[PDB]
Amino acid sequence: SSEESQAFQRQLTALIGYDVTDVSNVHDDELEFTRRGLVTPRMAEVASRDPKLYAMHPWVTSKPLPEYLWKKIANNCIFIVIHRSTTSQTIKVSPDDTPGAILQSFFTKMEQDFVLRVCGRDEYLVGETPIKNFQWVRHCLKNGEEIHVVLDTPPDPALDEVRKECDRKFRVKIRGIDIPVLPRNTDLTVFVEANIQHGQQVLCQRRTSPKPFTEEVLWNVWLEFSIKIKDLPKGALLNLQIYCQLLYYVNLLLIDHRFLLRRGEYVLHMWQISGFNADKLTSATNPDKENSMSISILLDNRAEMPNQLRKQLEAIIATDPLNPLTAEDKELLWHFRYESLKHPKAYPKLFSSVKWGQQEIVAKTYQLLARREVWDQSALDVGLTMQLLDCNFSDENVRAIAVQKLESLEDDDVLHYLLQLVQAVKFEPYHDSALARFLLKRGLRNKRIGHFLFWFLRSEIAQSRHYQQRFAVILEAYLRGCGTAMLHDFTQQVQVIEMLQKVTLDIKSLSAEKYDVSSQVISQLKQKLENLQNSQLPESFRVPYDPGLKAGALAIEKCKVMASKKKPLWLEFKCADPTALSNETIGIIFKHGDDLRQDMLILQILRIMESIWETESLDLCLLPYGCISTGDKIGMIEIVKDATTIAKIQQSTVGNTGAFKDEVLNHWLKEKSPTEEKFQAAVERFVYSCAGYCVATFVLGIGDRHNDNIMITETGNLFHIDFGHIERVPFVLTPDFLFVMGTSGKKTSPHFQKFQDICVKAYLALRHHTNLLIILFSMMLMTGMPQLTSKEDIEYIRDALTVGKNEEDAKKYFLDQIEVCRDKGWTVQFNWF
Ligand SMILES: CNC(=O)c1nc(-c2cccc(-c3nnn[nH]3)c2)cnc1N
């Protein structure tokens, strides 16, 4: 070691938010073994790094340019405006040409150590891509926007340097359980339940004879199982549970990370049930030694197929991910496993038909995984791959085929999936695994990815007792090879966030529940930000949720506390980049109160929902705004510019407890539209946004909202917010919205007609991915909700998506939805109270 080097670890810790050297909540070698394990991949990928494409992270894509999108292009002309200091000549260009082959078209049209960089951002039109395939360039087009770039020097790759570095049956003894205080209530009776467990598949289960719930209860029994030792699958968890009805659980992997059987004495600190979930799968023990329940244990150990079978097989294989398989089905899949292989889509259900508690069958299962000819040939399907990484699959090899498929994902597509792929690490049985390695591999390769990987890992580490150790290791593995420039920037980001959190907390506890912001609130708020500015606060930090943007000093005067029971901050920021061709402000909302892990999740999905709607050339104009969780009920949210709550729009002349009126939105639109053609822009925008957010919310099942949770931009763009949070209605299309569309009371019109077309297009577009959505949604609930049900709750989205039905019974369903809402109008709005 050095000292030094520990000073490194000292900063590494400050970024992680957790001690990876600390060993006080362990009982085996694995975390440190994974630290060491992750060095070879770190260092390979670091070694392969194209150093000049890495400093400049071109955010590009191989997806075609959407049609919509094409019909914003001249005659294969695209206008691009190069700047230099107090200068700027335009240069027309073709969509299908390179930033390598454009600078020279500048140099001509009146030394190659220059690069087209986006104005305002750290973002770069560099590398051998057609400029139409850069994401800013796609951004600018869609958002009727002008493409502005400053010619200057490539940043120094040197800045981005990395520093150098038995046929007996299984049996467990149950000694007893200890707990410092009961006083839950008076008393009851309790028994330990020992389950051996693979993919939330319970293999064998025993339990103790019941006994009286005291502070300490000894047993002191042996619980022998059916299963033999040679048959325990790798990944088998021993799941120890206490009933009275379930209140504590803990898990001990049986086979450890050296393929060695767990043996000997354990005293295991358990978790507590408080009010089918990812937390129950954990290898972690509760780090709180003083309060927790504790358990003590000792371990001392050719052909050709019939016609209608192929139909029953194909029938099963076609079914949804949430279809439960019968015994009958499973045996059918297994018997004809070699047929099953021909269809990649059968895989999930085929490996779900394996009996993993049989070493011989597991054997056969592996044999046919060596027959990956068709799988390795299949075009990548994420939805399918995704389901092999959920809680139903505990076998490394199975999971490993899933991760092989993920390498075809170019970065672009990683981003779309990252949050959930990170959330999939909670379903890994061991700390080191192909999924972790991959997340690291693919984070270290692209700065964009490395950034969001850092804020997704830090978010869980910050607030998940159940996983902070694992992620911490994975995060350190990242930080150790990411580049010292990334590191410096990260350190600031985290600093700014720690201050700004302090300020949003102090002001929470300085504010009761009286819907007023007092002078001495907006004094202490004002003062603190000043008394901070000024102190303390970096000259410049990079914006989580949007790392193109850096932000300088606070626009104190524009900062305010947002009239609400959580008193979130409404901070606004100067932009550190002189070349920013505006003086529009950077608007962060810090907030304590809600679980932002739920927002993130829903936003990810929405982004996926667009990309889907891209494949079919639909732009539904969603606004999935920035949002990063940074701790227990605490994080930030991007401020959509030029935006107002509907509820605020419905207060104008319209008073207070009095509401609402059918028009008022439309006037507000015009009270904001310059011309009359642009106003038509907005009403189209509105028809699209409105359809967008109804189809999505209906599906994710969160449509029924109070209208101060729903906003619009001055240019017509409607969008939900605060998914917080969640006589019922399937989504929010109220009378106001039907005005603007023009149909009062209830007849029809060309914009309500258009609105109907789009919605059906979008919804049915969504149904061309049923499997992907159900898998994301189910994963969503398991890794990010509290009170949840492996049936009814997840079984919602199937119905909502009208699983089973055809394109007509479908369109029927949804247009009824539209109508159910219409009856009906303000009923649920006024029902606020
Ligand atoms: C009045 N709200 C806004 O102007 C606004 N709100 C949001 C937003 C997004 C998500 C949640 C919230 C929120 N509402 N109450 N607390 N937090 C607010 C984003 N951009 C905005 N421009």
Image (tube, rainbow, N blue to C red):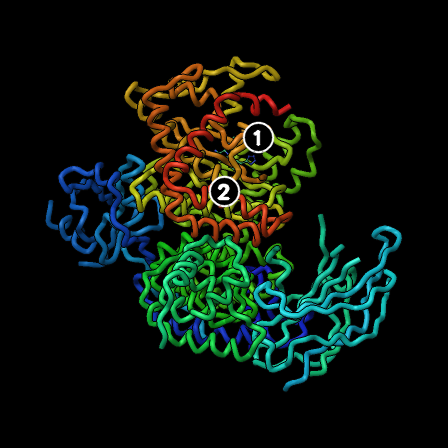
Residue 730 vertical placement versus 80 (above, below): above
Q: Nearer the viewer, residue 392 or 549?
A: 392
Judge from the rendering whether residue 757 lies leftward or rightward of residue 385; answer left or right.
Answer: left
Q: Residue furthest top?
A: 653
Disc number for residue 799 = 2
Q: Nearer the viewer, residue 104 or 526?
A: 104
Mark 2 residue crowding within 10 angstroms, few (<14) / some (14–19) / many (20+): few
Judge from the rendering whether residue 729 lies leftward or rightward of residue 407; answer left or right.
Answer: right
Disc number for residue 403 = none
Residue 61 vertical placement versus 281 (above, below): above
Circle 1 sits in a helix, a strand or a loop, which is it? loop
Mark 1 C-beta closer than 8 Å to ligand 1: no
Mark 2 C-beta closer than 8 Å to ligand 1: no
- Quadrant where the image shows the C terminus: top right
Judge from the rendering whether residue 733 lies leftward or rightward of residue 784; answer left or right.
Answer: left
Residue 531 x, y percent position in the rendering: 59, 40
Q: Dividing the picture into quarters, in which one does residue 177 lie?
A: bottom right
Disc number for residue 728 = 1
Q: Nearer the viewer, residue 254 or 39?
A: 254
Residue at x 27%, y 45% (from the top left corner): 137
Q: First in sequence: mark 2 or mark 1?
A: 1
- Quadrant where the image shows the N terminus: bottom right
Residue 810 x, y percent position in the rendering: 41, 37
